[PDB]
Image 1 (cartoon, rainbow over the protein chains, first blue to last red):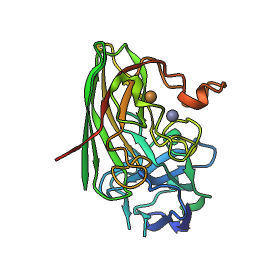
Image 2 (tube, chains in turn cyan, orange):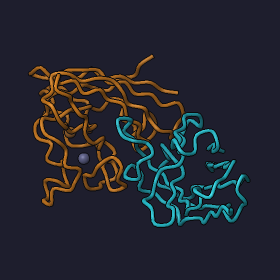
Image 3 (cartoon, chains in turn green, orange):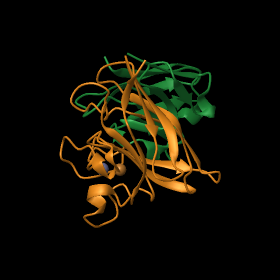
Image 4 (cartoon, chains in turn blue, green):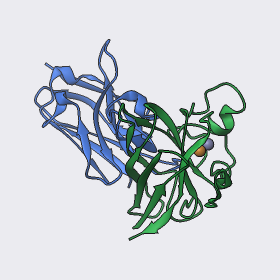
Length: 122
Length: 153
Ligand SMILES: [Cu+2]
Ligand SMILES: [Zn+2]
């Protein structure tokens, strides 16, 4: 799971993350983005289903972030970035999902990216 | 763009209907439907190799395992193609089922059309039971209901 994008941005600004899956045993069912802020527990941010349409967003990013899918790459368009969005952002995926489960829970994903820093100034 | 269906029946009260849908070859397969007559809690849920119902669920053979891996949970990479984990029955005994898996397929070599869907008496331990029976069947116990998986419109 190769991630690109990230870096520093001033508050209010925008940043695009992307993650391309390469060499995976099977096609992904859900693929998306989790994040871990300084000292906090990893939380789900946004995931998207194989269909490229069905999405799930943490309540804290609703309306500011939008995940989309190409290239079997996913993109996270982050707008209106605030200091509270500063975190290490991991791409994540599975090849199975039980819709009785929480699609933004870390335990429902076992493929993972190396991580990307995102820092929002001011 | 294939569809499939399975009517599950057994000697007892366990029965239900499970739909399959795959909009792309080598794409994920949606599996959904409902089972009733179950004791509350988790029940193993697997595709067995043969669609042979001549001796009830017994003639369905072992878990569908064309890659000769150990039994595991569906999330794992070390799993049988047929390992679909557990369904969960509420206090009424109704397990609503809605899952999606890209390991099974309705076409190609992992095709499960014409094989058997089986729901078990006990919970599947997902290969974590620490004995060799776990790495084979997950200790799901006896077969409460099964059906042959058939092509649907
Ligand atoms: Cu079974
Ligand atoms: Zn198995």
